[PDB]
Length: 53
Length: 150
Length: 96
Image (cartoon, rainbow over all chains, first blue to last red; front, side):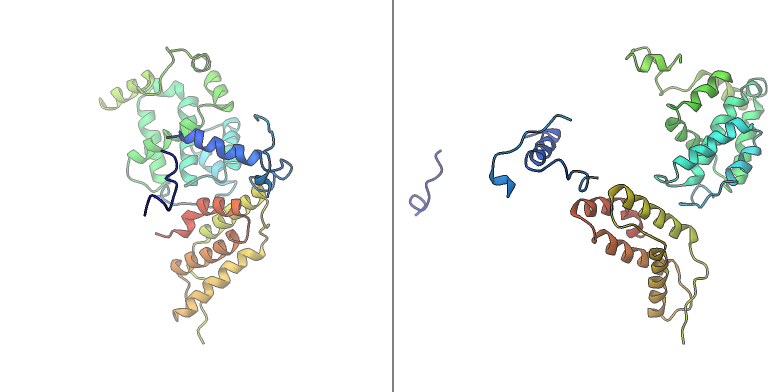
């Protein structure tokens, strides 16, 4: 029964690298005008571009 | 012991009276009081920072009397023990070694050792022959050698 | 009949709690703590002594009154402020 109920599909990140992707997801899906009220569906569209600083 | 008390409501005339007992001028006394005003929070025991700052400036100002008479260093330690109501000699050494690390990179601490650059020029340049804070200073080992002979 | 008093209390402990609570509400932009919040700690501490039929407020009733005001102020903010104030004020809540 396990050969007809599903298609059987087809067949270590660093700590700093994990936190960098979290902050990049916020800067690409949130406006930077309200950032001075939290740290001090937009995810269904294309992400926005931000700066390094 | 006064060092075990946490969160002590210190006034403005308490640090002034404590600095006058160690024979300190008004120039070095106002710098210690101003250091406590900017660092009112983010601390565990206020008595540990005041005792560590007064004894640190005592050896710099009275550096001419410690080299001639070795009994001045042994006497300035027992005086602070009676004011803090403590009997352990290890608490005084552990207090002056923690505040010195936080004041090792300021502006008022540099002018005090000059009037009363050779070490800061090697840390910024990345030199491998800089003075490492691991071994005991040469001027400190000569004092302990004379204290055990009296 | 029973009226508890505030004799033999840690006056330096209450001054350090309000000093750290007011300093965190300004840098984070939370609710400003006036002098009315300081008197609320003594009112809760006096109510705890009445539950034990005691005429004096010891150090156990003072530590419980601070945790009530802290839990009522931290949870009354945002999500980022709740995760930040719970780590700095965890020393006064976790009693010895």
